[PDB]
Image (cartoon, rainbow, N blue to C red; front, side, top):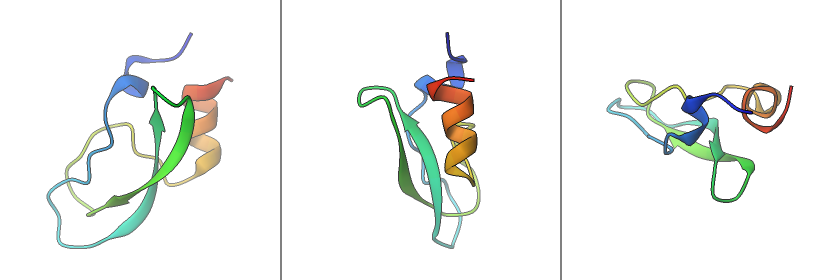
Length: 59
């Protein structure tokens, strides 16, 4: 099975920018794009789709 961070929601955070990041959506079982503000947020936040896939889909 997958680590508990995979269950966290997408969190845009508290910062002043916008950049593309990837999160694992538990309800869809997919790694999807979100808007990250550059600060704050949670560990379900990947710069590379591949890293979300290895962490939350399957090793």
